[PDB]
Image (cartoon, rainbow, N blue to C red):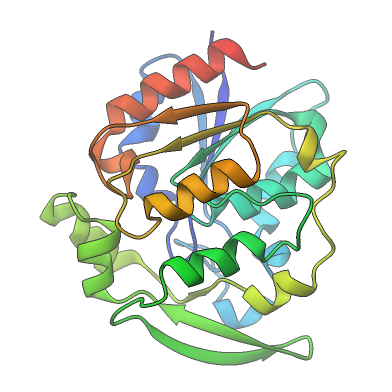
Length: 256
């Protein structure tokens, strides 16, 4: 079967991390949309204009709103992208055939929206040469960050080529986890987000979303299906592009 995949990047990244996976999925016959979220990739906004993870998710929400009745997509979110999936699923669950988490955070419905992020910051507290700043938006102080080049090299793009790591130094932009905003956000709902099919893809070789964090998430909120990719790194759509496309073909064949 063929599906319409909507690939969702993580904070500080853009559609560009999917540049190897998107042609591979199209060569299997799939339709693929790779979005730039707010203030991400070549989106015109700067991060200081964005006051929450929900505002950050506007390109994804606008995309789903534009789908005609009856058209369903499979959302694919990497790293912090699981939070965009959860926000989207609480507004457009009828339009989501399934959600695939790719070395991704997996929010739940029983604890606050920041819960899994608070746990990630406990398991991985040192983001090395990453710099931080603050800005004010809608009466709240938001902590912005710019991913450090050594963190990018060693923990996110560990086994990626020098030309792939070069794209990350050139294209990663200022972003935010909006952690304190997620902590006061209304919980994700059981009827929206809780109802969607959730496929969790990961590798135990991920150097930032470590096995203790990812196995903790799998135990916290049981996925419908789990795929473990052997080897690779945190950016599996770059180091294991073929294996991710094979898993996504199986999801397209299982969930519609």
